[PDB]
Image 1 (tube, each protein chain N blue to C red):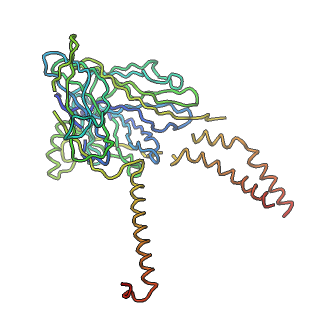
Image 2 (cartoon, rainbow over the protein chains, first blue to last red):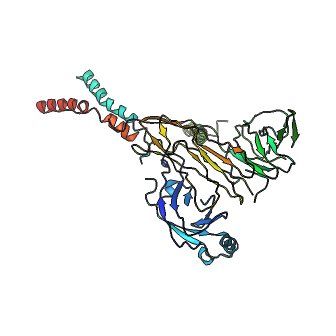
Image 3 (cartoon, rainbow over the protein chains, first blue to last red):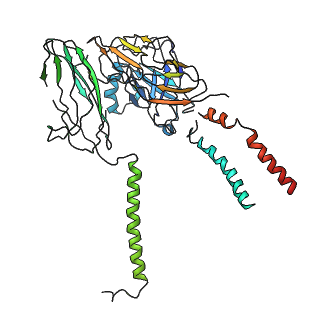
Length: 145
Length: 158
Length: 152
């Protein structure tokens, strides 16, 4: 539980085409198989002061935010065990910092390159019809001269 | 570990919001329960006798031994606007034996939503309506102002 | 103590990422209950064999673990064969709950069809299709400019 071997495998998420599509969830897979026997207990993930609902682990941090408001991959997410979460539940009302409670460990995430494309990948196909306006202008000229 | 519980997270339901319910029933009976079908549909709260809307119910035929539970999900989106009116949501265990008859062993729940807009694009329709009303009132006002201004002192008009 | 079980629905994210892109099906879990589930089953029963190929033949994955330690596999690599119309039929995700035993038959089927044309002869496809005809773009303009230079 001390993260003796900090396994850090970072991979990003496609997040579809967040500019046009609505499935805008940035869920980066930072795999962390540390020297721990974490099992049958909800290892709580506090990232930017927000406690993510942890299911089967999550190690995949999922910020379900719009791309315009989630163009960030670097995050310090603190993993707290059951006792640390219980202590935090009482310490938070006391205006105590996240780092003044005995934690389990911490993870640093770096996934710069958020959202990676063009806004419209299909409407530009219809723009090929604009080239026929040149021959239409030529036909108008033929009508004229 | 876990026990029987039915839930729906967050009460921020916009207009015509889709509400989902998940139910897991711990079977306290003396025998394994084989639920053939489940009852779930929205209707008029005061008069539940008539079926104004029949919500789709997928057959499940779930089998659970006693003191265990199974989880099932449903999702209903009110086509007609609604607010501040719970519906039935009655839980009926349809367990049948080799005899071929089902014995009804039946609580209620709540549902509510705040209505602002609806349609393919409700916001643009409401904005267009507001703009049309503003334009008609403004054009009437300016017509009256032009009629009044292009005269003498409007005191002998009476 | 609560529900919020598996909800691994297959969404129509991109339908076009890169040339020769292999679909990376991912499964999402959101549960807060303190209990655990056993005997996971991942079956690719409803998949298009003509346009998508499964890595490990007929995928039948059993995990039977609820732990933040790790998971067997949730990144299904569907390898396409050739360009065309691909349908995201469904992905079978059942659970043989050790508490009860019978199969929790759940598979999210969606009518999501997407078109990816020939990459070489959407964006790359249509761009290559448009730029295929070179003479029709330049030769009339070449003649127009020749006439202009002869007349101006």
